[PDB]
Image (spheres, helix red, strand yellow):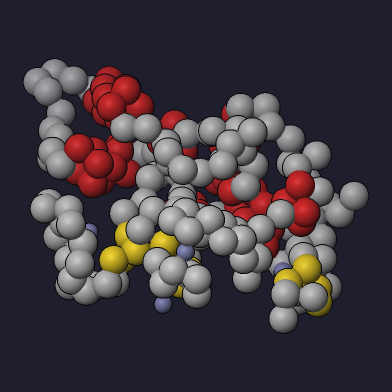
Length: 192
Ligand SMILES: [Zn+2]
Ligand SMILES: [Zn+2]
Ligand SMILES: [Zn+2]
Ligand SMILES: [Zn+2]
Ligand SMILES: [Zn+2]
């Protein structure tokens, strides 16, 4: 199932633990902490980010693991579905407007395109990402070489390069391997 569990889900501040329900970033009204609603990492005002290697220090931002909704929400549903199929995780495309209840407690009510189960496009995508996260699926397994290059620069701070007489497939396998060994999926994302 998992569509039911998305729908029954609730957001807790990672600092104060106040429970909210209520944009990737969230402002805690109890403690004034700000954080990612997808991965719970901190969002830093200009220019409060403590990471010394941050090239984006003058903008409001957070650092997200590669399986945060902040990134996966840019994938097409199709591609997300492919991740899910490759790991034998079932998902809906038909319903068993939009059904998701929001605290304004009213339904989203937006138009529901074909194939997005009974949801709007944005909510369907949160469903898929929920799931991916629930089962700890690694997106990097569908990365093309260039996304793998971007990933190893973003998470390991190295610009990689093909070795001599390394074909694109081997290059890809090496980048994926190093990436999976050295950089975990989201460390605060709730898992099954
Ligand atoms: Zn804000
Ligand atoms: Zn708080
Ligand atoms: Zn995030
Ligand atoms: Zn930063
Ligand atoms: Zn919706």
